[PDB]
Image: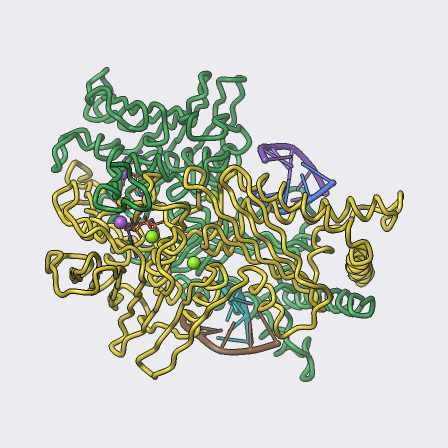
Chain colours: A yellow, B green, C blue, D purple, E cyan, F brown
Amino acid sequence: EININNYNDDAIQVLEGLDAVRKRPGMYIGSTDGAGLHHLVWEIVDNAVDEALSGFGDRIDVTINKDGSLTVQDHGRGMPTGMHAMGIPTVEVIFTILHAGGKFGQGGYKTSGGLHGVGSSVVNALSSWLEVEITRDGAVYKQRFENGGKPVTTLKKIGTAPKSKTGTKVTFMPDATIFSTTDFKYNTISERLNESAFLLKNVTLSLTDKRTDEAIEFHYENGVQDFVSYLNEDKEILTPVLYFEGEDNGFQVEVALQYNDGFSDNILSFVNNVRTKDGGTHETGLKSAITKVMNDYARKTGLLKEKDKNLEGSDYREGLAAVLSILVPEEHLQFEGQTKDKLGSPLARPVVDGIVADKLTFFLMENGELASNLIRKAIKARDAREAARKARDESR
Amino acid sequence: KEININNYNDDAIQVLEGLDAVRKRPGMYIGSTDGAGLHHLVWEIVDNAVDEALSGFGDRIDVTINKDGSLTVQDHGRGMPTGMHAMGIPTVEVIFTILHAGGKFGQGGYKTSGGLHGVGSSVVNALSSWLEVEITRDGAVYKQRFENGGKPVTTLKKIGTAPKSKTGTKVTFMPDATIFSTTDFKYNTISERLNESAFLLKNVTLSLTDKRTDEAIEFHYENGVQDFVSYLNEDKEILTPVLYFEGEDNGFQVEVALQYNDGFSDNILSFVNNVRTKDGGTHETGLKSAITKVMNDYARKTGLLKEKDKNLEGSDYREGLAAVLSILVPEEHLQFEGQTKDKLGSPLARPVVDGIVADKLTFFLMENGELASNLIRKAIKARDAREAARKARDESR
DNA sequence: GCGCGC
DNA sequence: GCGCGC
DNA sequence: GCGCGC
DNA sequence: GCGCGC
Ligand SMILES: Nc1ncnc2c1ncn2[C@@H]1O[C@H](COP(=O)(O)OP(=O)(O)NP(=O)(O)O)[C@@H](O)[C@H]1O
Ligand SMILES: Nc1ncnc2c1ncn2[C@@H]1O[C@H](COP(=O)(O)OP(=O)(O)NP(=O)(O)O)[C@@H](O)[C@H]1O
Ligand SMILES: [Mg+2]
Ligand SMILES: [Mg+2]
Ligand SMILES: [Mg+2]
Ligand SMILES: [Mg+2]
Ligand code: NA
Ligand code: NA
């Protein structure tokens, strides 16, 4: 028996690929509650988005099936349908081998949200079954896996299609012995597809729920500008939609900003179309550029006098809605963790900072009345903050 | 033919070997490749030594920053196994070169441990331009060396003898300067982490020696989270004694110490199997829930909150609060978010902590009524200050 | 100067 | 509240 | 009720 | 401010 007094070579165990995912799902998807369940949806949708980001496919359709499984169909290039160098179908490599993919800089993708080579295989590992259908060159191919990613068929030709059609259809049943819930939630998926649609010009994303026969689709022509208008939808706005974009050594930056009459700071950031809810270097560059340029404008126009302190970043972000979307070349791309909630790529900070600072400095100079109103707004925010502080300290 | 977006076929998919994948995507394993990521490597090697001590093996963990900028961690635990592993190579090589390979999957070699993924040592090796390990066991010292991201350059070889009973593991590594934006280990960063680790290991000495400047420091504490809380309040005026609560629940173990200072900040630290969870999670949620619920219940049943008064906010009771929560979670229930283990996900930790703390704190307040009523009056004043600030803010707008 | 993390 | 690094 | 994550 | 889950 293995115990603390018998700690020898058989006390060390090696978990084969997908078994490690099933044993330690928290390392790969963060949690095994509803947030982790929907993470599986995001891995499959993100792979369809990456095809669209490289130019392939104009529709991504998600279906919640009546049995509770979930399907994602795209019209991208399809997965490669041949034999892989390691002696199994490439499709089976994609779904069964961790750190196996096409987004390590080889050239099959332009900038993509995918980069670790694990998402599809993680979905397969954490599903009681998974099926994939690839359409390419007049044929449809299928492979099925069960019980956490074990192939039960090879990749087989199952039908034909028009010669020019292409795409990938993935259906999976999340493993009810892993997750505390396997109930996919319409609104959770709907909100995420809506966000993704803002970032993919003229791609339609849709959700159909066969459990209740409800469906919704999303399509936007104007990217982050439409997104900012959506954020301020149920609010009174105090400014037009400001739009800033630029490029820098393979990086691309787009940002839309608009003030509402509220006092909340509502900044959403994205890297290669992946939501980074916890921000990171790109959000840091945006926030720094705003504060530095607005303070410089305030001071050089005398709205902040010689004796006044600079305003705080939070003063300028009161009532601000902003959407920041950047594209980062694969060679510079670095996320914190499989969940990709934060961007670590150091170059994104000067990239975003430089582009935003340049465009905003010019915008303030050309729109002086709006600029001074924005500063006066931030000064009133400072006054309210300092009034609250004085009352809090006096109460104490 | 060149791989490009118009030639996306079977050769466009590449499979990365384990350590190669770590080097290619370090953010997936250590979060970042700045100074925080650099020191993460230290925590992986230290955490393994702490896990030995948590199972009862070793009472001293010595960290050395060497003159060449490498880092050594030496423990006196059981040592890594020195034989041949079932997969074909020496066990030591499996530990350092194979991801998801280890002794903390429930097999029984460890009691409750901070390690659980089987990746930490192999990540440090992958991200080092060299690494050496020396194992002391069965009267001998064995050494193996790896270079260039984890490639063995020696076999595991005997390099000396040892007394029959002595055991331990010594790991030295040079972080890869081609990966990290800084490879300058920071004395204060490591010292702070070892200090926190010492509070949670009764009577284990942890030490740091920096050969670059010839400075050293040790940490050794007898009274656990109570010493820890006193440390947090060291440069402040305190308003209460150290309150200590502990309990057990179906293999879970909970300890918490609390003490108010005269400040207005809240300073709550949480740990799971001695791993700092800086972003909290289910155990910290349970603790915060229990405090708010029990303190509002006490305030209301004593009439300090009248019929028409709203309950106080959790932030009113945490003003000036210092608190150290340490829980032990059995392997079969243990689940962290991510390799950096900044947040506990284990669902059962919430009811476990909430139940133990609520029970103990309810009884404590009933038995210490004058102190309880003073703490409620303090939180009511915090409510008043928060309401005064909100009023003034709204009137300014 | 600035955001960030302690 | 302060040092760190961009 | 409570903390949490929108 | 509000729903979700413990
Ligand atoms: N819908 C798809 N269409 C075409 N190819 C796909 C599709 N989904 C996945 N692939 C291919 O399969 C590879 C592996 O996918 P996956 O395991 O999710 O890793 P990844 O996108 O490369 N990186 P990550 O998601 O960050 O783990 C991808 O890199 C693509 O080459
Ligand atoms: N100092 C040590 N003394 C004894 N055994 C050790 C020591 N360090 C590592 N090991 C063994 O090597 C195994 C693998 O270590 P490691 O790769 O760090 O993964 P881990 O501790 O199991 N889990 P994690 O650290 O969460 O990735 C451990 O589980 C132990 O069995
Ligand atoms: Mg992917
Ligand atoms: Mg997430
Ligand atoms: Mg470990
Ligand atoms: Mg950390
Ligand atoms: Na994969
Ligand atoms: Na390992």
- Residue B374 placed where, x, y %? 69, 65
Q: Viewed as shown, does residue A199 lie left or right of A112?
A: right
Residue furthest out toward the front: A163
Q: Viewed as shown, does residue A294 lie left or right of B3?
A: right
Query: Is residue A246 visible from the viewing direction of this image?
Result: yes
Question: For the point 13% across and 56% down, which residue is it?
Answer: A155
Q: Which of the 4 quarters of the picture holds residue A373?
A: bottom right
B50 in relation to A91, above or below: above
A346 in relation to B184, above or below: below
- Residue A205 placed where, x, y %? 40, 67
The C terminus of chain A - image quarter: bottom right
Query: Is residue A393 visible from the viewing direction of this image?
Result: no
How many numbered badges does the structure rendering display? 0
A180 in relation to B174, above or below: below
Which of the pair A331/A338 is nearer the observer?
A: A331
- Residue A145 placed where, x, y %? 16, 60
Question: For the point 69% across and 83% down, which residue is it?
Answer: B308
- Residue B34 placed where, x, y %? 49, 35
Which of the pair A281/A197 is nearer the observer?
A: A197
Which of the pair A149/B188 is nearer the observer?
A: A149
Question: For the point 29% across and 39% down, which residue is it?
Answer: B3
